[PDB]
Image (cartoon, rainbow, N blue to C red; front, side, top):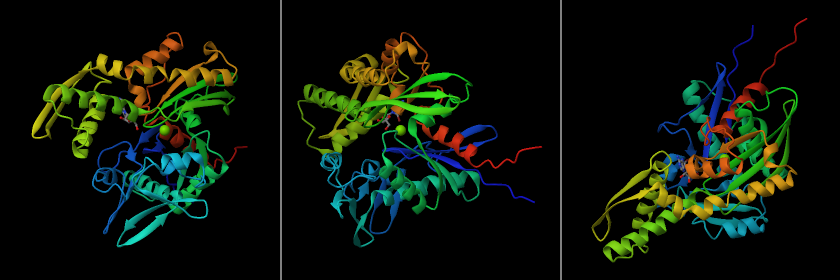
Length: 390
Ligand SMILES: Nc1ncnc2c1nc(Br)n2[C@@H]1O[C@H](CO)[C@@H](O)[C@H]1O
Ligand SMILES: [Mg+2]
């Protein structure tokens, strides 16, 4: 009579990493890609023979900086003249050009110079997330919910839908990232009465705090605040400067001018930073870092915490601003939700818990997966077509 319907997917289309989930058998499955990764880099690389997307693009970035595109989310739905765009362009190794006051990324691809709109680059990331899901389900996927930041305007939301349509996806709905994190915890299923929820989102390059009110499953964004110049990469930079100084003291050599050595040091620092979230110390072991000298050293969690102390404390300023804007007091917040990999940092959690006078933090859903989790829960709700009984 009626054939079984394919599952719909929830996609967190992130600035630096994207994540895909599916709700089946009363539970969400976050889908790992073919390299076993639960999150996929939002990177697209171009060569004379191939277009690479995800881990394959990010793993060759060092020798192909001009033709590897990342951060398209910072350009999506914006004008080329926008002050945000002009500032970001100074930090990017790829070319950004002006086509009718609309930014386009220009690269060498398959023997030609090619320019792409930000929605086209995002459609390539969405095609990879769709293929990750189809490899797990074993059938073609059509329907998806895609998330965006709460501060995205109409043009930014329409360009995200356009990216979905180019990728061959039927976009069920564009939902806000903090709303998706709240849905992941079922904070919209607690019944009658108003609930105030704070979402604390610390990413690779930006920090966002959102205050939502939930009443009978209805969401209202009460306040947004953040820091565009605060994220995981700033903590990596602090360890980089620390170890460059350490090499100078120990071997009387300045390494800061060999890009390969700085890159090898930064890659090692980012992994040591992750180890320090679960261990009280971490080792750093690089062979022939500079002038055939092996760099074998360590860093305690106490020293790393000291190195990033001002940065961690500065996350509380947008929290206080969001609470003033929402016209609420900290005691009036019912639930605290953590979003982003950088929230695993024990000191970040301690500062926030202390700010909210010992309150529990919702961190049981991996913070780098919570947004995709909630988008998957929403996607399964949106495709239901139940007919009422007599
Ligand atoms: N366990 C973790 N402890 C500390 N940091 C982490 C962890 N896992 C992830 Br993921 N990160 C950082 O999150 C950011 C996501 O873009 C990157 O800067 C990652 O380094
Ligand atoms: Mg995010």
